[PDB]
Every structure is written in C-alpha cells, then in structure tokens.
Image: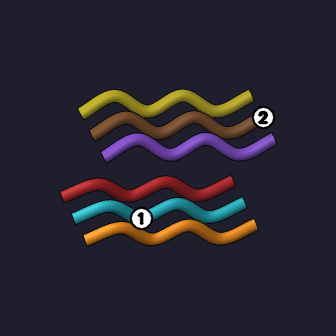
Chain colours: A purple, B orange, C cyan, D red, E brown, F yellow
Amino acid sequence: NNQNTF
Amino acid sequence: NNQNTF
Amino acid sequence: NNQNTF
Amino acid sequence: NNQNTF
Amino acid sequence: NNQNTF
Amino acid sequence: NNQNTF
C-alpha cells in the first residue's frame, strides 16, 4: 500500500 | 486530495 | 492532503 | 497534511 | 505501507 | 510503515 500526493 | 486504501 | 491506509 | 496508517 | 505528501 | 510530509 503506497500513496503519494503532490 | 484524499486517498484511502484498505 | 489526507491519506489513510489499513 | 494528515497521514494515518494501521 | 508508505505515504508521502508534498 | 513509513510517512513523510513536506
């Protein structure tokens, strides 16, 4: 489970 | 920006 | 920016 | 910026 | 479980 | 469980 937000 | 994972 | 993971 | 992980 | 936010 | 925020 990997989450990125700019 | 909203992210959910189970 | 909100991130949740179980 | 809010991050939660179980 | 990996979370990044800018 | 790894969390980074700028």
Q: How far separated are the C-alphas under marks 1 and 2?
A: 15 Å
In the visual, does F1 lie left or right of F6? left
Judge left or right: residue A3 versus residue C4.
Answer: right
Q: Position of residue D6 (x, y in %)?
A: 18, 58
Residue holding disc 2: E6
Q: Which residue shows up at 67% across the image and 39% down it?
A: E5
Residue D5 screen position, x and y as percent? 29, 54
Where is D1 relative to E2, above or below? Answer: below
Residue located beneath label 1 in the image: C4
Q: Is residue D1 left or right of residue B4?
A: right
The kind of residue on which mark 2 rests is Phe
- State the residue at coordinates (74%, 28%): F6
Q: Residues within 10 Å of mark 2 (few under 14, many from 20)?
A: few
Residue at mark 1: chain: C
Q: Nearer the viewer, residue E4 or A1?
A: A1
Whether labels 1 and 2 belong to a single chain: the reply is no
- Chain under callout 2: E
Mark 1 falls on what kind of element?
A: strand
Seen in the picture, residue A4 relative to D4 is either above or below; the reply is above
Residue F4 or B2: which is nearer the viewer?
A: B2
